[PDB]
Length: 190
Length: 294
Image (cartoon, rainbow over the protein chains, first blue to last red):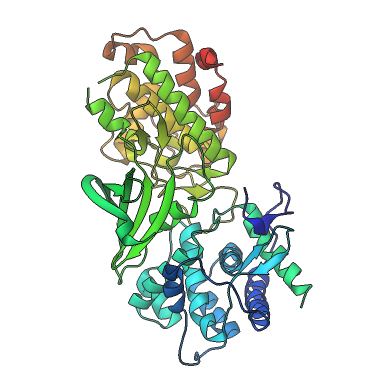
C-alpha cells in the first residue's frame, strides 16, 4: 500500500508545473505550519530510541545567522537547483512529521521546534539532491554553503535518513504532487 | 534494529561502496545478508545507499531482493537484506553456458522483476549477472539498486556512465541523456546471451572498443532505421557501414544446445540498436518463447 499521505491523489497525477520560487515558498510554509501544529499537540513520538537519538542531532543551541527564508535563498543562490529538489525536500519533512489515521485524517507524528529547523533544512535539501541527481555538489562545497562542518553534514544526512526510512520514500510524480497538496490541506486548518 | 540483533558471519562479496557479509538474526536463527556501507565523516553518505534505502518499503516483489532494516553504527550503515545463496555470475562460474530450460526460467524471473520496476517508473541501470541473486529453489531476484533512478522526473544532471560497460546500451555509450526503460532491456539481452554461451556478449575494455564490439555483431547504426541517432553527441556518420551478423551463428558454437527460432527472435527483440525498438519488459514476458509458462 502507498504512503498514507498520498491517499486521494490520482495515480496518474502530473508533475506540478511549479517554479523554483514557489517550490521554495511551499517548503518554508510547510515548515511554518508544522511549527504551528506542534505547539498544540503532545506527540506520540518515535517507535524507537534509535530514532530519538538521531533526531536530537537536529537541535541547534544558538540562533542561526540567517532566517529560514534567507538561508534558503543562500542555498539556491549557491547551488542553483531545480524545483524538484525542494518538492522532494518538502515531502521528506511531510513524511517525517505527518501521517493519516484510519479515517484518512492528517495527524502530527512528532513535534517540530524552531531550534530544529535550520539543520532540518540542510538535511532535507542534501538528501533530496542525492535521491534525485546523478551528480551532486561535493560534500565540501555543500558544507561551506550551509556553513557547517563536513562531519556535521554527514551526521545530518544519516539522521534524517534513519528518521524517514521506515516510511515509503520512493521518488515519484505523486510524491512531487503531494508536497503541494499536503500544504494546501494543512493551510486549510490553520 | 539494534546492532546486536544480527551476528556477522563470513564475507560474501565486495563493492566500491559496500561489503556484504553473511549474517544471522539472533532471535529467529534465520540467515540474512549484511550490506555494510562505510560512512566517512568527511565524504558524506553514499548516494547508492540512500537510493537503495528509498526503495525498501515500496518496491516489494517476488523477484526483487527484500531490504528489511537499516542500522547505524559508528562510521557504518548496515542494510539488512534477505539472504540469497548465490548470484548468477557465481552460479555460472560454479560450472559455462547453462541448459536452455534454466536459461528461460532465469530470464522469465529477471523480466518479471524488471517489469515491476518499470511499472513503478524505476530504472535499475546496473543489470548484470552479479546483481541477479539466486537461491536453492531457483528463485532469481534483482539486487543492488544503488544506481536506480526514477524516470519522468525533471533532472539537472545525467550520467551516461551508468551500467557496467559490458552491459551498457549503444545509445548510452554514444552520449544519450534521455534513455528510459530501454537501458535495462539492452542489459537483459546481454545477460540472455551470456547465459546461453557462458561468455560476455560484448567484453569491451573501454567506451570505443565497446561500441566496436557491438557494431561488429549488430551492424553499424542505420540512419534510416534509427533517424534519431543523429541527435547523439558521439554518433559518427562517417564510419564504414557493416551489416548485422547472423546472431545464431555467433552464439551456437559456444553451446551444445540447439538455439531455436523462438529464442533467437526473442533475443533480437531485446538487442535492437534503436532503443525505441526494444521490447518492453511486459511485451517480452508475453513473447512466444515463454508460451509454456502460461
